[PDB]
Length: 109
Image (cartoon, rainbow, N blue to C red; front, side, top):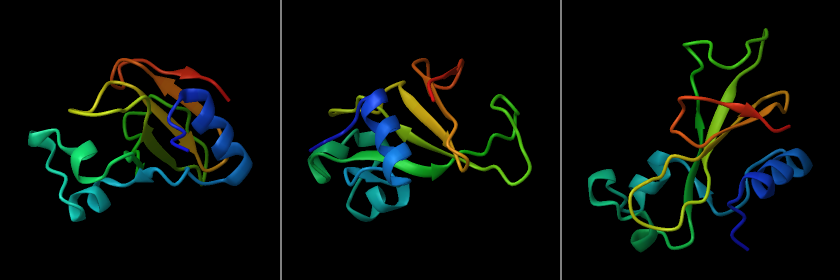
Protein backbone atom coordinates (compact mmCIF):
# COMPACT_ATOMS: atom_id res chain seq x y z
CA UNK A 1 0.00 0.00 0.00
CA UNK A 2 3.03 2.10 -0.92
CA UNK A 3 5.72 0.89 1.50
CA UNK A 4 8.54 3.46 1.00
CA UNK A 5 10.03 4.20 4.43
CA UNK A 6 13.37 2.98 5.74
CA UNK A 7 11.80 0.62 8.28
CA UNK A 8 8.93 -0.44 6.04
CA UNK A 9 11.14 -1.48 3.18
CA UNK A 10 13.83 -3.00 5.44
CA UNK A 11 11.26 -5.19 7.26
CA UNK A 12 9.63 -6.17 3.99
CA UNK A 13 12.94 -7.26 2.53
CA UNK A 14 13.73 -9.37 5.61
CA UNK A 15 10.31 -11.09 5.57
CA UNK A 16 9.82 -11.60 1.81
CA UNK A 17 13.38 -11.41 0.36
CA UNK A 18 12.23 -8.99 -2.38
CA UNK A 19 11.22 -5.37 -2.66
CA UNK A 20 7.57 -4.39 -2.33
CA UNK A 21 5.51 -4.05 -5.54
CA UNK A 22 5.80 -0.28 -5.77
CA UNK A 23 9.48 -0.67 -6.83
CA UNK A 24 10.73 -0.70 -10.42
CA UNK A 25 14.28 -0.60 -11.74
CA UNK A 26 15.61 2.32 -13.77
CA UNK A 27 15.26 0.49 -17.11
CA UNK A 28 11.68 -0.54 -16.23
CA UNK A 29 10.86 3.08 -15.34
CA UNK A 30 12.36 4.19 -18.67
CA UNK A 31 10.13 1.67 -20.53
CA UNK A 32 7.14 3.41 -18.93
CA UNK A 33 8.27 6.87 -20.04
CA UNK A 34 10.53 8.08 -17.22
CA UNK A 35 13.16 10.64 -18.29
CA UNK A 36 15.44 11.71 -15.42
CA UNK A 37 15.84 15.29 -16.77
CA UNK A 38 12.07 15.81 -16.67
CA UNK A 39 11.60 14.55 -13.05
CA UNK A 40 8.45 12.81 -14.28
CA UNK A 41 8.41 9.43 -12.50
CA UNK A 42 5.23 10.12 -10.46
CA UNK A 43 3.36 11.25 -13.60
CA UNK A 44 4.26 8.25 -15.79
CA UNK A 45 4.23 5.62 -13.01
CA UNK A 46 2.03 6.83 -10.21
CA UNK A 47 2.87 5.39 -6.83
CA UNK A 48 6.14 3.82 -8.01
CA UNK A 49 9.72 4.38 -6.83
CA UNK A 50 13.04 3.42 -8.34
CA UNK A 51 14.65 0.40 -6.73
CA UNK A 52 16.23 -2.99 -7.24
CA UNK A 53 19.24 -2.03 -9.36
CA UNK A 54 22.63 -3.50 -8.64
CA UNK A 55 24.77 -1.30 -6.41
CA UNK A 56 28.34 -1.89 -7.43
CA UNK A 57 30.23 -1.37 -4.15
CA UNK A 58 33.41 -0.90 -6.25
CA UNK A 59 34.70 1.67 -3.77
CA UNK A 60 34.39 -0.75 -0.81
CA UNK A 61 32.36 1.77 1.21
CA UNK A 62 30.12 -1.15 2.33
CA UNK A 63 31.52 -4.35 3.80
CA UNK A 64 32.67 -6.99 1.34
CA UNK A 65 32.36 -10.79 1.65
CA UNK A 66 32.85 -13.60 -0.86
CA UNK A 67 29.72 -14.03 -2.91
CA UNK A 68 28.02 -10.92 -1.45
CA UNK A 69 26.32 -8.52 -3.82
CA UNK A 70 24.28 -5.39 -3.19
CA UNK A 71 21.17 -3.65 -4.54
CA UNK A 72 19.70 -0.23 -3.81
CA UNK A 73 16.24 1.36 -3.46
CA UNK A 74 14.92 4.89 -3.24
CA UNK A 75 13.27 5.83 0.03
CA UNK A 76 10.72 8.53 0.83
CA UNK A 77 10.11 9.28 -2.83
CA UNK A 78 6.80 11.05 -3.58
CA UNK A 79 7.20 13.07 -6.78
CA UNK A 80 9.54 15.20 -8.88
CA UNK A 81 13.33 14.69 -9.10
CA UNK A 82 14.82 11.82 -7.11
CA UNK A 83 15.87 12.59 -3.58
CA UNK A 84 18.91 11.75 -1.43
CA UNK A 85 17.53 8.81 0.58
CA UNK A 86 18.46 5.24 -0.23
CA UNK A 87 18.45 1.80 1.27
CA UNK A 88 21.28 -0.52 0.17
CA UNK A 89 20.77 -4.24 0.92
CA UNK A 90 23.07 -7.27 0.48
CA UNK A 91 22.36 -10.80 -0.71
CA UNK A 92 22.91 -11.99 2.92
CA UNK A 93 20.45 -9.39 4.32
CA UNK A 94 22.64 -6.63 5.69
CA UNK A 95 20.72 -3.33 5.28
CA UNK A 96 22.28 0.13 5.25
CA UNK A 97 20.71 3.59 4.84
CA UNK A 98 21.96 6.87 3.43
CA UNK A 99 20.21 10.24 3.69
CA UNK A 100 22.99 12.21 1.85
CA UNK A 101 23.07 10.57 -1.56
CA UNK A 102 25.63 7.85 -0.78
CA UNK A 103 28.18 10.07 1.13
CA UNK A 104 27.68 8.22 4.41
CA UNK A 105 25.93 4.99 5.42
CA UNK A 106 24.42 3.68 8.68
CA UNK A 107 23.57 0.01 9.28
CA UNK A 108 19.93 -0.60 10.20
CA UNK A 109 19.60 -4.40 9.90
